[PDB]
Amino acid sequence: HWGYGKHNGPEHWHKDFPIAKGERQSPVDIDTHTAKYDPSLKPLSVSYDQATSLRILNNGHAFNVEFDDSQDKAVLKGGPLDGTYRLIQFHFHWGSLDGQGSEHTVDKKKYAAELHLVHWNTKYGDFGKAVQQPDGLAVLGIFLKVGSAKPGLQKVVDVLDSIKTKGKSADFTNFDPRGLLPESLDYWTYPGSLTTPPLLECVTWIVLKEPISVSSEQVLKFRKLNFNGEGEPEELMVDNWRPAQPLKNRQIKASFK
Ligand SMILES: CN[C@H]1CN(c2cccc(OC)c2)S(=O)(=O)c2sc(S(N)(=O)=O)cc21
Ligand SMILES: [Hg+2]
Ligand SMILES: [Zn+2]
Image (tube, rainbow, N blue to C red; front, side, top):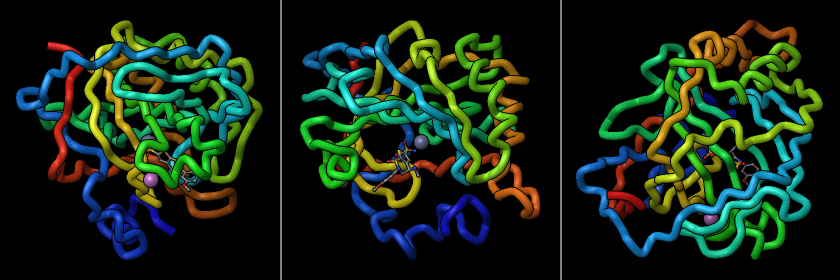
């Protein structure tokens, strides 16, 4: 299937997912100078106090920590959103080197990695339905920069040994996603899509201005994951990020000046 190799990378995805050349694709470059500061923008409402993590699994593209989205346990409201978006999973996109990994860039600047807390609009019933609507999903993107260790991230770093290869998973309960959030909830927002196939344009992107810092050894562990499954030639999971797409007839609105 698709991937990030020269033969099945982002530059080949259109052949199987024509929407790859659609009108509102992500990621995009966030030009801070021409992004319109919108004052009618309400503040974000992140309520992860009842968040219930279930497991973490390597899916061949990255590891995901899934959450029990059966009830309004961890939701995102406010900001550019209308309705309540329920958290279902979060993942990261990172690179082989420190100066690459984030999918979104700020003024062309790339970050070591990018965290995406994926939510789905509950007014649609289930997830599979939300992905059939232009406002079905809300992804909170957070930039990770190398520096001091992010305490709340270490719990995830420790478990990466038991899910080295594709298909593996492990119980990962009682994880508090709030330990991965920056101090400020200031953001940028625009309408976009998933950054991986099927590349659906159902996402309202909220990219926080403030990045979190993770240590070198922390992100280093990410790079030890395997794209491949057990018993197959080792293929390091690194650079599982998509390049920026044309903004086209879209504008980025900041919730700050
Ligand atoms: C591969 N995982 C991706 C697709 N996913 C997915 C899973 C099940 C069904 C489905 O479409 C019917 C899509 S997903 O919506 O959860 C996400 S969010 C996301 S990102 N990087 O833009 O935040 C990439 C993916
Ligand atoms: Hg959609
Ligand atoms: Zn992602």
